Every structure is written in structure tokens, then in C-alpha cells.
Amino acid sequence: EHLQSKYIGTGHADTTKWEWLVNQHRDSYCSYMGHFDLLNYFAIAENESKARVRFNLMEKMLQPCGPPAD
Amino acid sequence: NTNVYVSGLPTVDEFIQLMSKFGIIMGLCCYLKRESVELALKLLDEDYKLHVEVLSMQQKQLDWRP
Amino acid sequence: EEEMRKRKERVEKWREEQ
Amino acid sequence: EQKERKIMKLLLKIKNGTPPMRKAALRQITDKAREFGAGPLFNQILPLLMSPTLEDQERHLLVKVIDRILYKLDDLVRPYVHKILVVIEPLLIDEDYYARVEGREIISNLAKAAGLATMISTMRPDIDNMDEYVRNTTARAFAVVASALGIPSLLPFLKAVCKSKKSWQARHTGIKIVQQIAILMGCAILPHLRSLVEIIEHGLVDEQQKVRTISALAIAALAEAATPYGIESFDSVLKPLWKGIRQHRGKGLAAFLKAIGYLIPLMDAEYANYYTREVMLILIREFQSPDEEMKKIVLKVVKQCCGTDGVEANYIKTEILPPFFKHFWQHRMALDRRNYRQLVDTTVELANKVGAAEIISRIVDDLKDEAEQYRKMVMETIEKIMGNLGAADIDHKLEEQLIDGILYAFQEQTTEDSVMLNGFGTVVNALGKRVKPYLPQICGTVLWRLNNKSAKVRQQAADLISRTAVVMKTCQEEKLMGHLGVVLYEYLGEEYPEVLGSILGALKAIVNVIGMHKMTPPIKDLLPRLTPILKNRHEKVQENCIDLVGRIADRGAEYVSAREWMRICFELLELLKAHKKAIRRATVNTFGYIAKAIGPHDVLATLLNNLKVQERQNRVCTTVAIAIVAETCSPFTVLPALMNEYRVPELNVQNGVLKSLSFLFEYIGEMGKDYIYAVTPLLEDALMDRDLVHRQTASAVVQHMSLGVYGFGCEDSLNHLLNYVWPNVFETSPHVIQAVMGALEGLRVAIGPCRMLQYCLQGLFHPARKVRDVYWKIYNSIYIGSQDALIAHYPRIYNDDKNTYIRYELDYIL
Amino acid sequence: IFCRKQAGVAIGRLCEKCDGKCVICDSYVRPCTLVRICDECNYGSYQGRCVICGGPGVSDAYYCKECTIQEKDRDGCPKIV
Ligand SMILES: [Zn+2]
Ligand SMILES: [Zn+2]
Ligand SMILES: [Zn+2]
């Protein structure tokens, strides 16, 4: 329905692999930023500061899957 | 049988309104469906003392069409 | 009947206290 | 010229037509605003704003235009400020709150648009105007200018105005602006407060009575706005106010007393003492004042000072109460509603500090007074005080005076008064157990008034029983409550429904008190009398009658026959869907009692036969009734009967049991957990069946089952039902597909978003557009519903040549 | 259609005929969450409008339990327009 367009990350019958995966990756990084324990896990696994893990995730939000298909 | 006879009556105007509560109608009464007779015998008996003893569009009043 | 007897008592009893 | 006609067309498409026409036309005016120019555009808009015919919503939409053109035009408005302002200013003084706030909004926008210097240069010639009306609006204009811009920005202007030696009118208007700023801004004044007080402070000392008056009112307004903070700001003005309090007279003193009344609540307990005592030497003198404006003030100042924490309860008890009761609690004060409400409030606040009995003992002597309006005044005060504080403080010798006076007042009022009904009910309910000795006198007084010839007077007597039967329970209850009920039983034939509703509301109150065996009109006589009353058209009658039949069913089920109850249920049946919320709630509660009274079996058999033979209106009522017989009594007694009705090979009865089940699951909620496994195979048949309406309403059952059982397990049975819901995803009929979407939105909650995603994946990229449209519609509901949960549940998607699609962080190990 | 502007402090109201219905689903079962409406829908004449039909509001509008669970309280100002 039309009103679903109020909400970013919804799709439609001509949604591509790239559009759909870019929303999955952006939603994932936002989830990692919110869930303090999931952010703990990545900081320990990388041996990196929670502040740099958050920054690296924010940098990944721009182009999370590489450029659009063509 | 859906036909019912009634005694202890006071008009047709009263009679139809009074009996409509026991189910749809197409002194004596004629209901669409048999179960109206069970309701009449339970309820219209004693309701004066009232006393009681034993096309498409018409059926489409019982339908659950939205 | 108490009802009016006590009614009359109430009204007079104040105007005696006044 | 023609573009001005386009302004007319655009105004027309804002003032009339559908919201997108309005939205488009507004977008057009606002972006075109630069071209139209301020002069032409306001020459055309202001005549509409001046028209007497313009509605509030038309004016509001024209304001929603004016804001945006003012933003777009900006500096272009500067030549036209004067013309614009004089049309707008009168809105700031309109009695309509919305006309008023709208005027403030457009002066705010005009002041953001035009430079401050231009607003000042426009309005300055009106500071000095001879008309107080012009000054008054100008003061309100400048207050709005101050609100939109920074308060500090206007301060240097105010500093010049309040020292404008050549015109008292100017200095006066400056201080009006400072007053109006405080009234408009509220607590937002506080960081600028000392800057504002230091502008006013010299005015209290001035040689002009007008300027002293307005400066005292400015200080009152600032203190009001600052409450409870900011006392340190006012340290300047404390000395000038006392030096004035000791010296001024008339309304010029009333102004200073107003200021002081707002300052004392700001003070520390030590200063609150010192300065309250400073007040009383003069405020007690003003208790004698003839002036109604002064009398309004001194009651306000008493309320404010005695409400302050510092001032002793003993100080109030010794120095305030004797002159206060002397001058205000006398007959002449009842004559004016303004004074009346103010005196009642002030007096209740004295009670809050000094105690109930200290105030009530000075008042109760006048419950027995001559004058109705004065008896009303004392009764309203006792009503409020004992509502606040209760009976604890009151001596036995004060009960006697209260009750004697209360009885006298009730027997005295010629016309039914709500206040007397309030006061009597409050005092009796507050006293509670203590009322026992007086119950004969109370009962006799009620019974007398209940035998009165007037409709309204008996309505009030029945209302009083309704509010107080709980206290009357105390003793000889069977004897007294019972005779009150027999009198009420006579009035069950009332010609007036307003009265009958109260008779019923009084009978209801009696049966919530009496043990049903001790009823004086026996239940066998009571119920038949009520059976014709259930059919009364009037809401109050229906409410109280249904609710009373409720208590008879609840508390005294045994006194009447199964068939008597059965007939009552069948009459109540349609009231389950009545327009009024009260009538429905009464019917639902009481059908629930009568279902217990009858026992579930034959009431249900009767309801299932009704469900087969009535019109859609009464058939939906039976679905509600069957669910009440499930939530009340036993659900396990209902479902076996419904299962059997579904075995009848007719589409109309089968469709009926599906509506019954759909409402039963909505209605019983969390109870549904015990029943999913039993109802499951019926829903298989229903959801496999050819009929469109079977599949629609089996889907609706699944929605309500799902939302009802969330968190109680049962996901095994709901997964199983999803295998029969899901094939209906390609149905095209509006009603079946909305019911299927409803079921899926239910199951997303009870089975979770992971499962719903597992059903979507193979369709999101399916070759056929008609599969994709449907699957993306479902996915979008799951996604909007559960966006953060889906993170865990998305499948692994492998990388391509150009693009990375693995989520590596979730691949990490610890 | 529903208004779906961001809701504010204003409480939604219901007329006597629509009293106790859920604005979203029109069920009368278990009112749970207070309806909140946008300022525009509660301004001037619009103030006090029944959420469902725009009549004078005699009672506060309430979203049902089923709607509250589905977070349908959260979609925005449910004033029907
Ligand atoms: Zn709902
Ligand atoms: Zn809205
Ligand atoms: Zn309505």
C-alpha cells in the first residue's frame, strides 16, 4: 500500500538485489549501533575501541555493498 | 413445520412486531426457518397471558455476506 | 405518622434557637 | 493585473475544495510571493482578514498563508508594516482565544520578517497616543514583538520609554509592555527577570498615580509568571511596596496589595513571616472596604499569604480568622457570584492550613440561617472542606451542629439544589460510622422529601439515597433501607424518566446494601415491575434498570425462575449493541450475571437457535452474547456446542459459528490458550472450504486467536494454521484479502517475524509480477512491524563480482 | 483515510454513538492505549472532534489491546479524514 512509502527500507515488485541488500546492511549497522552487547562482541573480536567500531559502522552506512549494479 | 398458532392475543400491527423477535417472518404465523418455533415455544408462551402451539432474497436475509 | 410531626419540629426548633 | 486575478484563483483554491488543491495553491502563492510583491499581495489579503464573514478555519488557513509569504517576502514588508499592523492589532484584543493566538502568530512572523528597528519606528508614535485603547493594543503588539525576538533586544527601547520624562502616557505604556510581556511569556521570563524588574522599579516611586498603579501591576505579573522562583530579582521593589502599602488608598492601593500577594509565595519562610505581618496591618483595614474590586484583591492576598509555608497556623487562627469571619461570612456576601466563588475558595484554603474544625465551627451556625443563597454558600464551603479533609478533626458537639443544620437546610430549600445534595452526601459519607445516632432523623427527612409532590424534589431525595445507602447499612438497616425501598417501589411507575432513573439508581443502591432475603418489596415483586422498564427509551432509565436487574441476577439469582431469566436475556440481547456506551456496559455485565443464574447450557442452546434465524443486526448481537457466556461461566461449555453447529451442512449456520468464534477469541483474550488445539480442526475445514466468507472469517478467527495467545506458547498450532492461511494470499476479493492480511499481521506477533520471513523469501523475486506485488505487500507489513528483529533472520546472500552481500561482523567468533 | 501526521500532546475524543470503539479497527473490545492526535486536527473547530466521525467528543478515544500489541498506536494521528 502507498503509506508503506513513509517507511524507508520497504520494497516493491521492481526492487533489485542491490536495493534490498543495501537496506539489510544499513538496518544491520543501525541495529549494531543500538545493541550495546552486539557492539561489545565486535569490539572484542576486532580488538578495537567501541568508539572506533561505531565510527567504522557509520562510515560503512554510505556504500555498504559497493556501487549500484549499473 | 414453521407455522405457529397463538392465543390470548390483545392487531396485526402488534402481532408481527411481537413475533419478529423470534426470527424472520415471510392468530397464525409463518417463520422462514424451523428454529423460530423452538424460540416461540420457549419465550412467547406466557409473555394478558400469551399462549402458543405448533424466495431467494428471503433466504438471503439469513446470509453472512459482508 | 412521624414524618410531618418531625418536619414541623425541625423548622420551629431553629426559629426558637434563633 | 491578471496575476492579481491568479491570487484570487489561488485564494479560492485554498478557501474552497479538496486539501491537495489548497496545498498546491499555497505552494504556488508562496514561491510566487517575490514576484507578486508585498504591496499588491497585502492590499488583497488584508480585506479578507478584515471581513466579518470569515470563519475561524478560513482565518486559520489564511494565517497558514500569511506565515509563509512573510517568510518569503522578508525585508520586502518594511514599507507596509504600518498598514499590515493596524489591521492585525485588533485580533490581540478579540475575546476569541483562537482569533487572539492567530493575531499573535502573524505579529510574530511579521516581526521575524521586518527589522526590529522598523517595528519600533512603526509602533513608537502609538506609545505617546492619548487613547488608552491605542496604548493597550500597542502594549500587546510590543509584547508579541518581544516574544518572537529576543527579550534582551527590546530592553534598550524599554529603558528609554520608562524614563521618557515628557509624557506619562509613554512611561505608562512602557510599563504596560513590561506587564504584557510577563502575561504572554510565562516562566520564560525568569532569566530576563531582574532586567525587567530594574526597568519598572522607579515607577512604584513616581509622582503619577497611573504610573504607580501600572508598575505595581507589572510587578504582580512578573511575580505571577516567575512563581515559585526569582525572589532575588524583586529585592529592589520590596521596600517601595511597603512604603506604598502604608501610604496609598483606593484602587491605587489595591494594585500594591495585588503585587504583594504574588510576591509573598516567592519568599523564604522567614521573609514570608516578616512580610505577611507587614501586610495584615493594612489588609485587615481593607476588609472594611466598600469596593468590590478591593474585596476581590484582599481575598486573593489572604489566599496567597495563608497558602505560603512560613506563616503560622496559629498566626492565621489568632489574627486572620476573627476579622475575616466578621467581615466576609455575613449575608451580604452571598449576593454576587464573583465574590461568592472567591470567598468560598479563600475559606477552603484557610481550612487546608488551620484545619477543618476551626473553619467549619465558624460556618456551621449559619447552615440554619434564613437566606437560601447564604445557606448555599456555607453548604458549598462545608462540601469542599470535608471533601478535602474528612471528618477526623470534627468534635462530637460539631457533628450535632453540622447534622442539625444540614437537615434544616435540606428541609428548607424550596427548589432542588445540587449544592444541598452534594453537601448532605459528602458530610454523611465523611462521617460514616459516626452517623449512626442521627440515622432516624436523616431517614425521616429523606422519606418526607421522597413523599413530596414535586418530580424534581423526589429526584433529589432518590439521588441522596443513591449517594448514601452505604452509610445507612450501619444498623436497623433492614428496617430503614427496606421502607425507603418500598416507597421507591411505588415510584417505579414514574411519568418522568429523569425521576425513574433516580428511583432505579436508589433501588440499585439498596440492593448493593441489603441481604436479599430481607428485601421489603420481595424480589418476586421487584423483578416483574422492572421487566417493562427495560424497554423504556430514556438512557438514564435503561442504565439504572439494566444495572439493577444485574444486581438481582448477581446477588439474588434463586428468587426467580429459569424461564423468567431466559425471557430477560432475550430482551437484553439487542442492548449489547446499543449506541450508548453506558447501556452496552450495563447489558454486558448483567447478561454475564444472568448466564451464571440460568447456567450456560440452555441459554447457549437458545442463543445458537437465534443465531440461525434472525437479521444481521440481531445475529451479530448473538455473537456478542455467546462470547459473554464463554468469558463468564465456562468457555469449555460453549465450544462443544459451536463445534456441533458447524457439523450442520448449511453455509449460513456454518458461517454463523465462524463469526461467533471470531468474536469469542477477540473477547476472551488470554483465555484462548486452553482452546486453540480443540478449535484448530474446525479452522482447517473452514479455511480449506470453497466459500469466500468461510475463508474470510476463519482468517479473522486466526487473527484474534494469534493476538490473544501471544507469549503463551501454542506456536505449533499457529504454524499449522499458517499452512492453511498462506494459500489464500492470492485471493482477489477485497474482504477475503484484507482478512488474510489481518491474520498474517496477527501471526507475525504470535509466531514471530522469522517465520513470516521464511514464508516470503521464495516470492520476493519470483518471475511473475502478480506474485511479487503480493509478496512485497506482505514483506512490507512484516518489515514495518519488526524491522530490528529481521536483522537476525535474513538469509546468507553471497557476494557478486561488483558487490559485497555477506555480513562479516556476524561471522566473527569469540 | 487516516491522517498520519506525527501525534502530539492532544488526546483524541469520541462522540456517544462511537464511544468505546477503536479508531483503527472499530472493535469495542478491551480499550488499552489513549489515542493521541496532531495539533492541526485539534485546533479551533477541529478541537474536540470525534476521531472517527468529527462529532462533539463526550469521551477519550482508546486504541484496543490488539492494536496496541501490533504497535498500531504508533503509525501517527488516527483522525479519519
Ligand atoms: Zn483496534
Ligand atoms: Zn491529524
Ligand atoms: Zn463519532
Image: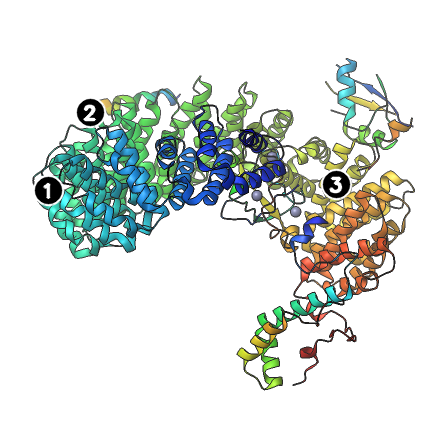
In percent of width and height, residue D256 lies at 16, 40
Query: Residues under labels 2 and 3: Cα distance?
Result: 67 Å
Q: Is residue D363 left or right of residue D539?
A: left
| Location of residue B11 with respect to D620 vertically, above or below | above
Disc 3, disc 1: CB below 8 Å? no
Q: Is residue D670 left or right of residue D420?
A: right
Identify residue type, mark 1.
Gly
Numbered circles on residues, count: 3
Q: Which residue is mark 1?
A: D244
Q: Which numbered circle lies on residue D623?
A: 3
Describe the element under mark 3 as helix, strand or loop: helix
- Marks 3, 1: nearer the viewer: 1
Q: Which residue is mark 2?
A: C18
| Other-residue count near label 3 (Cα within 10 Å), few / some / many at <14 / 14–19 / ≥20 | many
Name the residue nearer the viewer: D29 or D414: D29
Describe the element under mark 2 as helix, strand or loop: loop
Query: Residues under labels 3 and 1: Cα distance?
Result: 77 Å
